[PDB]
Structures are given as structure tokens and as C-alpha cells.
Image (tube, rainbow, N blue to C red):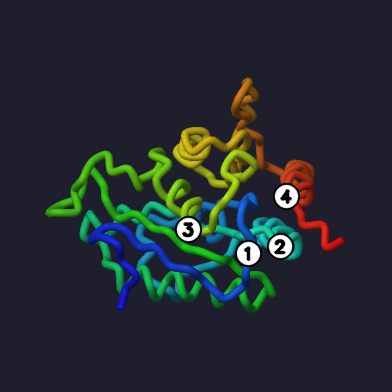
């Protein structure tokens, strides 16, 4: 069965790694961040990883920091595809990551969108980024330290969701910096900027002494 908590919300624990409580997480958007973005992410055969995200996932994995995918899937509300297609596509993304030796620990997805047709056409649902619901829910489920967590995505809504969830930093794929008290949008445009992100993840790593 699809792990739906309601008709437009999917929440799924991935793998069986154990995380002690009060860890920070690495939150990642999916389309445009982990995989190449596309208008209609319904065909698993079309999925291609963004290799420049793989060092970040690997770093978090090795640091013992949970990696949490938080993705809006408005195409579901819009009738472009359904949860079965999401399951196939998302599974393919996780398989490709496995082949690169990296993994994630939880997937949350929100179908609701204002331009939908039918009962999923809920315009401002708490789980739909920029609303922080998926981050807050992952926080409850994994007992996360949200204030120390990081988020990476290619849309402003990812940065807004992070700020609203209580994070202090996020990295905007292909985006510009916006450094303010309380929240910094960090640019992620080249390998130097990836380094900044990796340093930030590494500082969160476990001391096994």
C-alpha cells in the first residue's frame, strides 16, 4: 500500500539505519536537486541524477546525519499522474542513489495544489512548501534538531519552508545569496559553494568517542 497519511500526503521511512534523537537533518528537495527537474516526473525511465548533489548525500551519510527528502508533487493534484507513478519514479531515484553508494532516510511528499482539479485542489495546505509542514513532521518522527538542520533545493519555496521551520541556513541550487540575521540563503552554483555546504554538514557529524 502507498504510505499515505491523507489523500495528498505521503510519508515513508527509508532503510533501517538507526538515528539517536536530537540530531540535525539534511533536508533535500527532489526534482531539481537530487534528480534533473522535469515538468512531469511520472516516467521512471526518464530519471537522471544530478551528480553534483551526490557529494552532499555521501557526506551526510558518513556523518550519521539523516537525509530527508521533502518534495511537492503538484502533478498529482493536476491529474498529470498519481501516487503509483510517484512510487515508481521515487523508487528509481533511490535505486540510482544506491548504485552510487548513497542513501536517504525518509521521504515526504505533498500532492495538494491550487490549480488541481478535484478534491486534491487544496490551495495552501500546511504540508505544501513554502509551508514548513513536511519539515516539522519529519522533525516529530525522527526527533530532529530543526534549528541546526540544513535544507538544499532549487526553488525559493524550499528556502522559505526551511526558514519557517526554524532552520538558520539553506543552500539554493543555482541561486543567489541572501544573508540576513536569523536566516541565510547560501548560493550553490559551483564546486566552491558545494564545499561550503559540505563543511556545514561535516560540523554536524557524530563524535564516536
Is label 1 or label 4 in front? 1
Mark number, residue 64: 2
Identify the residue under disc 4: 201
Task: Kindly state the secondary structure of the residue where label 1 is placed.
Answer: loop
Distance from the alpha carbon under mark 1 to that under mark 4:
16 Å
Q: Considering only order in the chain, which callout, 1 or 3, is on the residue closer to the N terminus?
A: 1
In the image, residue 187 sits, relative to residue 17, either above or below, namely above
For the residues labelled 3 and 1, say whether their Cβ atoms are less than 8 Å apart: no
Is label 4 or label 3 in front? 3
Q: Considering only order in the chain, which callout, 1 or 2, is on the residue closer to the N terminus?
A: 1
Identify the residue under disc 3: 141
Q: Which residue corresponds to the image point at 42% horizontal and 71% vertical from the top-left?
A: 89
Task: Kindly state the secondary structure of the residue where label 2 is placed.
Answer: loop
Distance from the alpha carbon under mark 3 to that under mark 2:
17 Å
Mark number, residue 19: 1
Q: Position of residue 131 (x, y in %)?
A: 38, 39
Q: Considering only order in the chain, which callout, 4 or 2, is on the residue closer to the N terminus?
A: 2
Q: Considering only order in the chain, which callout, 2 or 3, is on the residue closer to the N terminus?
A: 2
For the residues labelled 2 and 1, say whether their Cβ atoms are less than 8 Å apart: yes
Mark number, residue 153: none
**Is the residue marked by circle 4 packed among few (<14), some (14-19), or many (20+) residues within 10 Å?**
many
Amino acid at each position: 500500500p502507498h504510505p499515505l497519511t491523507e489523500p495528498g500526503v505521503w510519508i515513508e521511512r527509508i532503510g533501517g539505519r538507526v538515528f539517536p534523537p536530537h540530531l540535525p537533518a539534511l533536508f533535500l528537495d527532489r526534482d531539481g536537486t537530487i534528480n534533473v527537474d522535469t515538468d512531469y516526473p511520472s516516467d521512471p525511465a526518464e530519471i537522471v541524477l544530478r551528480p553534483q548533489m551526490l557529494p552532499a548525500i555521501a557526506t551526510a551519510n558518513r556523518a550519521g546525519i539523516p537525509v530527508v527528502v521533502v518534495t511537492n508533487q503538484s502533478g498529482i493534484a493536476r491529474g498529470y499522474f498519481g501516487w503509483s507513478a510517484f512510487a515508481a519514479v521515487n523508487g528509481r531515484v533511490l535505486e540510482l542513489l544506491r548504485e552510487e553508494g548513497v542513501f536517504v532516510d525518509m521521504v515526504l511528499a505533498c500532492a495538494y495544489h491550487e490549480a488541481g482539479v478535484g478534491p486534491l485542489a487544496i490551495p495552501d495546505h500546511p504540508m505544501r512548501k513554502p509551508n514548513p509542514g513536511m519539515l516539522v513532521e519529519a522533525g516529530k518522527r525522527l526527533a530532529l534538531d530543526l534549528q541546526r538542520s540544513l535544507i538544499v533545493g532549487d526553488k525559493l519555496a524550499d528556502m522559505q519552508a526551511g526558514k519557517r521551520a526554524g532552520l538558520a541556513q539553506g543552500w539554493l541550487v543555482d541561486g543567489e545569496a541572501a544573508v540576513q540575521p536569523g536566516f541565510a540563503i547560501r548560493p550553490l552554483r559551483d564546486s566552491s559553494e558545494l564545499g561550503d555546504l559540505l563543511a556545514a554538514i561535516e560540523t554536524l557529524g557524530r563524535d564516536n568517542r
